[PDB]
Length: 53
Ligand SMILES: [Fe+3]
Image (cartoon, rainbow, N blue to C red; front, side, top):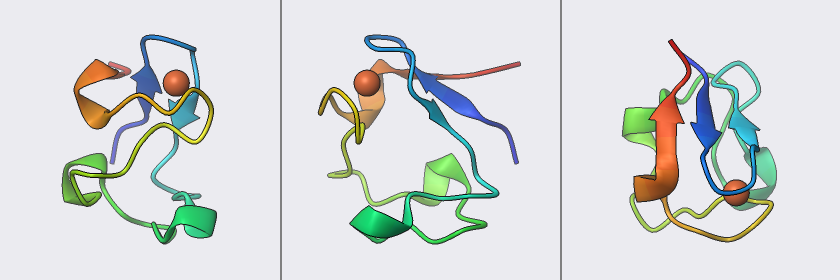
């Protein structure tokens, strides 16, 4: 699992940590995050994120 960054605000989704406050548990791959989840920082959707390669 890769980290992904919100290209609008620079928030990094790290799959080891998930986003548990918003119901994304540690170990969720980004592609498995429900498609209505938004960046916890700026609130934009998933389509503004890019795999950190
Ligand atoms: Fe963001």
